[PDB]
Image (cartoon, grey):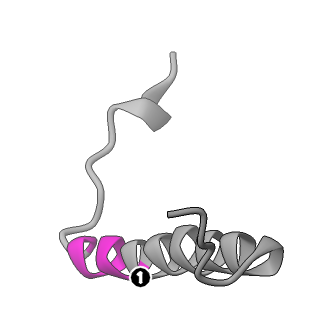
Amino acid sequence: RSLLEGEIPFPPTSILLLLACIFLIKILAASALWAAAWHGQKPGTH
């Protein structure tokens, strides 16, 4: 008896997913650039 799993989500939803995406890429990107620069910006060793 777990009716909580058989209920449909309210028809609104998709816009919420878009908000998640903006949060996601914003983190994964900013952290990465901050790292490589913090060691050396534009490293040489060509």
Q: Does residue 18 sit above or below 9 in this rendering?
A: below
Left or right of residue 35: residue 19: left
1 or 27: nearer the eye? 27
Q: Magenta-highlighted stretch: main secondary structure?
A: helix
Q: Quadrant of residue 45?
A: bottom right
Q: Quadrant of residue 19?
A: bottom left
Residue at image mark 1:
22
15 magenta-colored: yes
Q: Amino acid at mark 1?
A: Ile
17 magenta-colored: yes
* Residue at 36 percent of width and 77 percent of height: 16
SS of the residue under disc 1: helix
* Residue at 33 percent of width and 70 percent of height: 17
In this rendering, the count of numbered labels is 1
Q: Does residue 41 sit above or below 6 in this rendering?
A: below
* Residue at 59 percent of width and 72 percent of height: 44
Left or right of residue 17: residue 12: left
- The region drawn magenta spans 13-19
37 or 5: nearer the eye? 37
45 or 11: nearer the eye? 45
Which x, y percent locates residue 4? 48, 36
